[PDB]
Amino acid sequence: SMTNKELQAIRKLLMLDVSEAAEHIGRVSARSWQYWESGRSAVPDDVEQEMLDLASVRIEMMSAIDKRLADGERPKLRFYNKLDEYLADNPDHNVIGWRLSQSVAALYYTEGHADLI
Amino acid sequence: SMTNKELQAIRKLLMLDVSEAAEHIGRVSARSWQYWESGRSAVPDDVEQEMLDLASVRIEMMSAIDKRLADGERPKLRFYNKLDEYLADNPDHNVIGWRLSQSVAALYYTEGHADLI
RNA sequence: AUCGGUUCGAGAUGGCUCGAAUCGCUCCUGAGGA
């Protein structure tokens, strides 16, 4: 059972906007998502499960970069500034994968391990 | 020199809004900060220096939680929903420390090391 | 006019229906205006 604070924490960590999360994860309007983050309405179960699943996918993304850093190379990571240039390189992905790509790449750029292209 | 992608990456990692960074870090209008992130105008050096200094404060905070994690403790971290609630417990801080606190609390909640109150 | 971001207000309160402030896109002459 979630809490509005930790729901907002997971949403802000994965670099999602309110309307993007409302359309693609909630399937609700943005006002309903704002009422879930405010505690006026209780967070549903499936939203909790899907956000925990997306955090697991983020851990699977970080494991391969740790695997490459174990091999002594220095990775180059793609930081797409716009969704259309992301979809030019990615046929079968959406805005969630773009946000996950940005949130994974920003971490390893800030820690000094990798480079952004 | 710092590219616009790296500036946007560090800004989105620290959970700062455009207007907040434009007022306190940039001391400019938000229209100019969008030009620095869009690539129409070059990033000034004194913004680069400030963002790297702030990221070092974040690394210091993560080390400070990790030294408590080394004791076998399960730390209960504080996530603040509002700026005035943070200012009640931190009279001499401002909005930047609130955002940094929120990012560190979200990161340690997500990976299972900590609990949120 | 139209379209985006952030923060909020009501209502037999439901994953619902209506609204508000402000910053932008656009136009003019690290800035100011409608």
Image: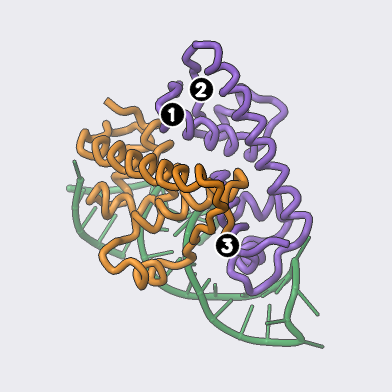
Chain colours: A purple, B orange, C green
Say which mark, if any, is on residue A5. 3
Disc marking residue A94: none
Of the numbered discs 1 and 2, the one sitting upstream in the chain is 2
Q: Which mark is residue A77?
A: 2
In the rendered image, the quadrant that contains the N terminus of chain B is top left
Q: Quadrant of residue B38?
A: top left
**On screen, C11 above or below A20?**
below
Q: Distance between the residues labelled 1 and 2?
A: 9 Å
- Residue B50: percent from the left, percent from the top? 25, 41
Place of residue A58 in the rendered image (x, y in percent of width and height, measured from the top left): 63, 36
**Element class at badge 3:** helix
Instruction: Name the chain under label 3.
Output: A
Residue found farthest to the top: A72
Circle 1: element type: helix
The kind of residue tagged 1 is Tyr
* Spatial separation of the CA atoms under disc 2 and disc 3: 31 Å
Say which chain tag 1 marks.
A
Residue drawn at 42 percent across, 54 percent down: B101
* Of pointers 2 and 3, the one earlier in the residue sequence: 3
Give the vertical position of A45 relative to C27 (above or below): below
Count of labels in the image: 3
Query: Which residue is pictured at 35% across the width and 40% down the height?
Result: B55
**Residue corresponding to mark 1:** A109
Using the rendered image, report if marks 1 and 2 lie on a common chain: yes
Q: Which of A6 and C30 is in front in this view?
A: A6
Q: Judge by depth and name the residue closer to the eye, A34 or A43.
A: A43
Observer-nearest residue: A66 or B33?
A66
Describe the element under mark 2 as helix, strand or loop. strand
